[PDB]
């Protein structure tokens, strides 16, 4: 149908079979495997498995996920382990992508993946900077995006959008100073969610 | 013999068939120290034995390359080297063991 | 309650790392005042350092202490390597912010905040 | 006396506005349209606005892009090192008042919190022609100055 | 020169403002007697480090809670 | 010792300000420490307070030299979570303006690369061409740069009558303009002395450091997302991927110049193969209806009202979608919670990994070779900092 | 499909060697570059005589905002607040109440022109063509406050530019 995205059945079967393959080989760490309706394979693993799972996917002959495309974190405050660490990998040999996910909380360190992918060095610094997730055995873990001395982790869901402090130049002390934030116009929160369900296929149980 | 692999930092190999035979044999030797029921051993042994058989039958380097479907023969050598490195690490990690810990009840539920 | 540690396995291990951080901060203040040509005294800078350590004295969670030490070391490096500018080092003192009323009557006069 | 001072301001105002050497902070997007003003279609050099300068040889600073809290101290320091007379042109919504990142924790809500601004050029980005209009508006502002007339009447 | 050790050690503590000298007796405990805090002791150990030109790791520094112990450590 | 490269050149330049903390011994670079964040504006957190349409303009302002390519990446990610398909004419328009954008980026990449090295004349010749391509942007969208033209569902408006002929006129003469650029640089011994064997990166190191685009292809890696993982109608156009052999700045410079020629080759096919039809998905629950429908039909007005207030809801899910942007692989990890605002939007900027490799690529080079190496990576700190 | 950008082997016959030696010693490839810049000196420049000449624009150009009227003179805006809802920058602030004749009209209509991204989403969202981005782009000011438009300023912009705004809309409304 002209307006509907076509389904690719062959890639869904292929990625499912490879998902079982990885689950069978790494049972010590793999907690869940799923493939989305648009054919993206996700491996959910225990956080202890970061290095073994990423090394297997990089080096194994049937995996060869040589390129770390992205590494990010998602904050879900309702979860006991609020932070979800997402690794997106690319295999040039098999022209395929895979997503590997794990989790942690505010006080639990994750193992640095710099040994597996040098690309991860700055990504982990950004996750530390913006979410406050510590990576153990990182060559140089420090803020990368925020200002020096910045307090808090702005990408956390409970960090306010405009922050807590703002900058201006003060003539009395002849330097830029930081003061508690005041807004001439407050950001206008909108309630946009319709009170009618949109997607029955995703309904949660009562 | 080629003049270049085409990939910067990847050198041509003068004796690709012999180098591959060494590497696949070393991999199978290392795979012997993994428990027989580990899926890693069974699967890695299967693919290694398929590649080794292809190296035995095909003497022409060009023709062998279309069989292995792994790029330049030097890329195939490099991959065997990585597999051998991986197999050693799996002996320490032992990923064939039961899942270390279950996630909390709603760890992987989306949407919340 | 069995949790993965950061560095310290108990509070006595953590308190050691805290004291090393204090020594490093204590010794750097005279250099910080000079390199950044601050107009505070070395005693003023050290008093602020004590103030910052003091307001975390109630913590009894070794993991939280490790993060506090980890964050404190990063701040020291930014200062030692001169990544901070003069403006950054002086933000600990809030020189341009008028004192905030603390008692009930003073807060009642100014507005509605408690 | 009165006549001379009037003609003398006319001279120095002509010289300063006919030779406006800019320092551009190419902070972000707006620096692209700033480059298009130097490109052959508009050729800012033909107005006397040279291509390259140096902070310590510049007369006008063009804040062309978003100014973050991290960048704020460095921009103020460059402004403080400019020899006088010095002017600031605020180019685009970000530099004007924060623009599309106005409500961000890490963005200065207008560069006029850090430095005094002579001209505000609206747009996101302002077209190269819009910036050129703002630069020629600053020349008219300089043409209106009366430094010696005021000085002579002190 | 051992007896000099006492003078230097007891001299450095005099210069430290938090210790009223009327209560500064060589055997006085920094915490119980002089009423100092843990970080005050760290400042003293750092003050001794400059006077005697050597370092004192935290392992040993936490066992010096009165002037006499400092004297014992330095001589040894 | 220890230095700090200036924020930017003395001449006008548009790629952002960098604080580069350098370790040197004699003339040699011992360490490069890029201190970024000077253009970090919290885009990803802002996107969480916007509907999916309201967030689209944030993508023009990332790699703000490749505006429509960034839009296309975001649109493909949203269209994938929506499970819809943009109409074929929109796909051809998106590939057509994708290649026009690639020309815009490569002109900026190559001529500012020469301008920083001191070869400044080609900059002026080639931004007269960029000025004419800005006119194409403004004629379809009304804006010279930040068009907000490509959207989930297709494109906002259809090409004005007479635009395609003008694009043909521009494309007719452009190869000669590339030829004049090559006359100044390609065989110039000074240009080669500044670029040949500078910033060599091995194929394996490039992959492990997370490089993409020309940073991979300069080292001989045969990878182009338009070929291997095609999107829109890129599988219906013919072009060659330029491949380097020595992995240095000079080979990457030649790759970009050849990619410009292939973009002209692709644009030629888009002009000849442009099909008729609608420009946005005929699905008024995603794409707003025509203004004439909105003013006559009750259903159309309701859908116009809801699309421009609440916005369309995206089924819950997460996708990583990437395209072959002019600067390398540009991707978005977009998380939907079922509402009309994205839950999380991570932006994968190709220059983020590339600038992380500057320390590696500059080992054992001169202080002025760092200028060339940041040049060959083509860094825009809008996308590096978000 | 791929191609090599730099995979040529130089010819080592004495003639080719001598050709490269002449290029090195006589700078011939440097002379060739001088010819190209010389050819430009005698070309006609691309510069236009601003402000007497202007860059070409199209009817779609997104410039300064304006509030429009019906031919009767009644305001088109009915305070529906769709533009305020869609504005990516939250640059629009609207208040409304029943007019003395009961008409649904705004009492406040502000656009912070230093927040605006000049994206045109408001004029797409407007159901009555009330708010538009006009063709004016030469409105830089000397103060920040002059870029905080209220309803009087925007209505005056509509009365000022309507002659051209209406023509631009007439030329493009069939693409919308
Ligand atoms: C010592 C020799 C100095 C000679 C004075 C040079 C002044 C030249 C000049 O004013 O040009 C005419 C200028 C040209 O006018 P203009 O500079 O204001 O604008 C020209 C028209 N546009 C800008 C549109 C191109 O006339 C004046 O503006 C009056 C300035 C008088 C200053 C001379 C003081 C004596
Ligand atoms: S004002 Fe617009 S074009 Fe200029 S830097 Fe900000 S977002 Fe980019
Ligand atoms: S042009 Fe865009 S940013 Fe400006 S007022 Fe209209 S909707 Fe808001
Ligand atoms: S300008 Fe248009 S969209 Fe905005 S409130 Fe008025 S009628 Fe509604």
Image: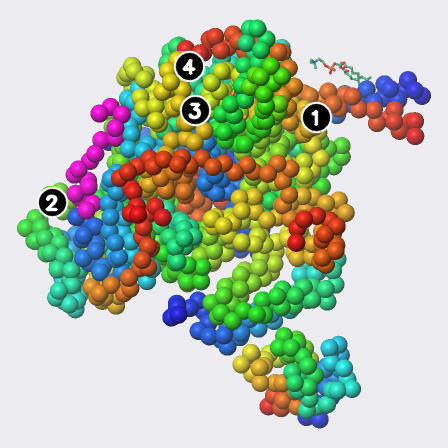
Q: What range is drawn magenta here?
A: A1-16
Q: How packed is label 2: few (under 14 Cα within 10 Å), some, or many (20 or more)?
A: few
Q: CA distance from mark 3 to mark 1?
A: 38 Å
**Residue underneath mark 4:** F295
**In the rendering, at what x and y percent does residue F383 appear?**
46, 39
**In the rendering, at what x and y percent does residue A103 appear?**
36, 56
Query: Is residue A10 rendered magenta in the image?
Result: yes
> Which is more toward the observer, C108 or E48?
C108
**Residue underneath mark 2:** B67
**Residue underneath mark 3:** F305
Residue lying at the far right of the rendered structure: D1
Q: Answer yes or no: are tags 4 and 1 on the same subunit.
A: no
Q: CA distance from mark 2 to mark 4?
A: 64 Å
**Residue underneath mark 1:** G142
Of circles 4 and 1, the one toward us is: 4
SS state under label 4: loop
Quarter-wise, where is residue F269 in the image?
A: top left
> Which is more toward the observer, F133 or F230?
F230
Of circles 3 and 1, the one toward us is: 3
- Which residue is drawn at the image coordinates 26% and 42% (left, top)? A36
Of circles 2 and 3, the one toward us is: 3
Query: Is residue B99 rendered magenta in the image?
Result: no
Q: How packed is label 1: few (under 14 Cα within 10 Å), some, or many (20 or more)?
A: some
Contact between marks 2 and 4 (CB within 8 A): the answer is no
Instruction: Examine the rendered structure and indicate whether residue G121 appears above or below residue A191.
Output: above
**In the rendering, at what x and y percent does residue G121 appear?**
48, 24
Q: CA distance from mark 2 to mark 3?
A: 60 Å
């Amino acid at each position: 149908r002209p307006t509907v995205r076509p389904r690719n059945d062959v890639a869904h079967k292929q990625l499912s079979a490879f998902g079982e393959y990885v689950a069978e080989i790494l049972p010590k760490y793999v907690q869940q495997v799923q493939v989305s309706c648009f054919n993206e394979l996700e491996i959910c693993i225990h956080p202890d498995g970061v290095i073994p799972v990423l090394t297997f996917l990089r080096d194994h002959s049937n995996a060869q996920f040589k390129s770390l495309a992205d590494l990010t974190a998602v904050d879900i405050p309702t979860r006991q382990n609020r932070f979800e660490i997402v690794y997106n990998l690319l295999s040039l040999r098999f022209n395929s992508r895979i997503r590997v996910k794990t989790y942690t909380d505010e006080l639990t360190p994750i193992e640095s993946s710099v040994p597996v992918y040098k690309a991860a060095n700055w990504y982990e610094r950004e996750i530390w900077d913006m979410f406050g997730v510590f990576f153990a055995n990182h060559p140089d873990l420090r803020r990368i995006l925020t200002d020096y001395g910045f307090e808090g982790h702005p990408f956390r869901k409970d960090f306010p959008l405009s922050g807590y402090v703002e900058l201006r130049y003060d003539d009395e002390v002849k330097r830029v100073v930081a003061e508690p934030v005041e807004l001439a116009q407050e950001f206008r929160k909108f309630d946009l969610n319709s009170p009618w369900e949109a997607f029955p296929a995703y309904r949660q149980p009562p | 013999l080629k003049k270049t692999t085409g990939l910067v930092g990847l050198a041509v190999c003068e004796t690709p068939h012999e180098r591959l035979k060494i590497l696949y044999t070393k991999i199978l030797d290392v795979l012997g120290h993994i428990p027989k029921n580990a899926a890693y051993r069974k699967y890695t042994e299967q693919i290694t034995n398929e590649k080794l058989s292809m190296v035995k039958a095909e003497p022409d380097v060009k023709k062998l390359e279309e069989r292995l479907q792994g790029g330049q023969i030097e890329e195939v050598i490099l991959q065997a080297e990585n597999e051998l490195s991986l197999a050693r690490k799996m002996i320490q990690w032992k990923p064939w063991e039961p899942l270390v810990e279950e996630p909390p009840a709603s760890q992987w539920k989306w949407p919340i | 309650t069995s949790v993965k540690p950061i560095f310290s396995r108990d509070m006595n291990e953590a308190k050691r790392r805290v004291r090393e951080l204090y020594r490093a901060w204590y010794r750097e203040v005279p250099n910080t005042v000079h390199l950044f040509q601050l107009d505070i005294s070395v005693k003023q800078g050290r008093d602020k350092v004590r103030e910052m350590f003091k307001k975390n004295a109630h913590i009894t969670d070794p993991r939280v202490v490790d993060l506090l030490v980890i964050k404190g070391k990063m701040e020291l490096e930014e200062t030692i390597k001169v990544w901070k500018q003069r403006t950054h080092v002086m933000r600990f003192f809030h020189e341009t912010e008028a004192p905030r009323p603390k008692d009930f009557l003073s807060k009642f006069y100014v507005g509605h905040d408690p | 006396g009165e006549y001379v001072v009037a003609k003398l301001d006319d001279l120095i105002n002509w010289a300063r506005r006919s030779s406006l050497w800019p320092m551009t902070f190419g902070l972000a997007c707006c620096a692209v349209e700033m480059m298009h003003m130097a490109a052959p279609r508009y050729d800012m050099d033909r107005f006397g606005v040279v291509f390259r300068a140096s902070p310590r040889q510049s007369d006008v600073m063009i804040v062309a892009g978003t100014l973050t809290n991290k960048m704020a101290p460095a921009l103020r320091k460059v402004y403080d090192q400019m020899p006088e007379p010095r002017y600031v042109v605020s180019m685009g919504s970000c530099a004007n008042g924060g623009g599309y990142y106005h409500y961000s924790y890490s963005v200065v809500r207008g560069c006029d919190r850090i430095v005094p601004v002579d001209i505000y050029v609206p747009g996101c980005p302002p077209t190269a022609e819009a910036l050129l209009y703002g630069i020629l508006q600053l020349q008219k502002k300089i043409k209106r100055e009366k430094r010696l007339r005021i000085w002579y009447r002190r | 020169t051992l007896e000099g050790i006492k003078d230097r050690v007891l001299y450095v503590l005099k210069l430290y403002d938090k210790i009223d000298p009327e209560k500064l007796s060589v055997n006085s405990h920094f915490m119980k007697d002089l009423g100092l805090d843990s970080l005050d002791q760290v400042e003293i150990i750092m003050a001794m480090e400059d006077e005697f030109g050597f370092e004192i790791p935290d392992i040993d520094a936490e066992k010096l809670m009165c002037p006499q112990e400092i004297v014992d450590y330095i001589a040894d | 010792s220890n230095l700090t490269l200036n924020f930017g050149p003395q001449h006008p330049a548009a790629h952002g300000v960098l604080r580069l903390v350098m370790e040197l011994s004699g003339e040699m670079v011992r360490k490069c420490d890029p201190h970024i964040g000077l253009l970090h504006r919290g885009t990803e957190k802002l996107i969480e307070y916007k509907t999916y349409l309201q967030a689209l303009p944030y993508f023009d302002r990332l790699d703000y030299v490749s505006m429509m390519c960034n839009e296309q990446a975001y649109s493909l990610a949203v269209e994938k979570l929506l499970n819809i398909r943009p109409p074929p004419r929109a796909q051809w328009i998106r590939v057509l303006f994708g290649e026009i954008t690639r020309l815009l980026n490569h002109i900026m990449a190559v001529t500012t690369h020469a301008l920083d090295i001191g070869a400044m004349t080609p900059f002026f010749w080639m931004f007269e061409e960029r000025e004419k391509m800005f006119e194409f942007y403004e004629r379809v969208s009304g804006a010279r740069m930040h068009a907000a033209y490509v959207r989930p569902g297709g494109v906002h408006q259809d090409l004005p009558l007479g635009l395609m002929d003008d694009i043909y006129e521009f494309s007719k003469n452009f190869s000669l303009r590339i030829d004049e650029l090559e006359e100044m640089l390609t065989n110039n011994r000074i240009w080669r002395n500044r670029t040949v064997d500078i910033g060599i990166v091995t194929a394996e190191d490039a992959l492990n450091y997370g490089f993409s685009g020309v940073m991979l292809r300069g080292s001989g890696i045969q990878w182009d997302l338009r070929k291997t993982q095609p999107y829109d109608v890129y599988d219906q156009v013919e072009f060659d991927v330029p491949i380097g052999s020595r992995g240095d700045c000079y080979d990457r410079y030649l790759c970009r110049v050849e990619e410009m020629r292939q973009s002209i080759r692709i644009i030629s096919q888009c002009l000849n193969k442009m099909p008729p039809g609608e420009i946005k998905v005929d699905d008024a629950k995603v794409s707003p209806p025509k203004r004439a429908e909105m003013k006559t039909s009750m259903e159309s007005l309701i859908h116009h009202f809801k699309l421009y207030t609440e916005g369309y809801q995206v089924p819950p899910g997460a996708t990583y979608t990437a395209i072959e942007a002019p600067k390398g692989e540009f991707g978005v990890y977009l998380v939907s919670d079922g509402s009309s605002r994205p839950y999380r939007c991570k932006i994968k900027a190709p220059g983020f990994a590339h600038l992380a490799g500057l320390d590696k690529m500059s080992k054992g080079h001169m202080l002025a070779d760092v200028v060339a190496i940041i040049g060959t990576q083509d860094i825009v700190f809008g996308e590096v900092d978000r | 499909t791929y191609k090599y950008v730099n995979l040529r082997e130089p010819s080592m016959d004495m003639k080719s060697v001598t050709d490269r030696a002449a290029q090195t010693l006589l700078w011939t490839e440097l002379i060739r570059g001088l010819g190209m810049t010389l050819s430009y000196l005698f070309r006609e420049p691309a510069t236009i005589n601003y402000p007497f000449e202007k860059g070409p624009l199209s009817p779609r150009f997104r410039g300064e905002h304006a509030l429009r009227r019906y031919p009767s003179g009644e305001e088109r805006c009915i305070a529906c607040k769709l533009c305020e809802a869609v504005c990516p920058a939250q640059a629009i602030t609207i208040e409304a109440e029943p007019r003395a004749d009961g008409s649904r009209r705004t009492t406040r209509y502000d656009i912070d022109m230093t927040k605006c991204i000049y994206c045109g989403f408001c004029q797409e969202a407007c159901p009555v063509d009330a708010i538009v981005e006009g063709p004016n782009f030469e409105f830089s000011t000397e103060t920040h406050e002059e870029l905080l438009y209220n309803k009087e300023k925007l209505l005056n912009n509509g009365d000022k530019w309507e002659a051209e705004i209406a023509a631009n809309i007439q030329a493009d409304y069939l693409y919308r």
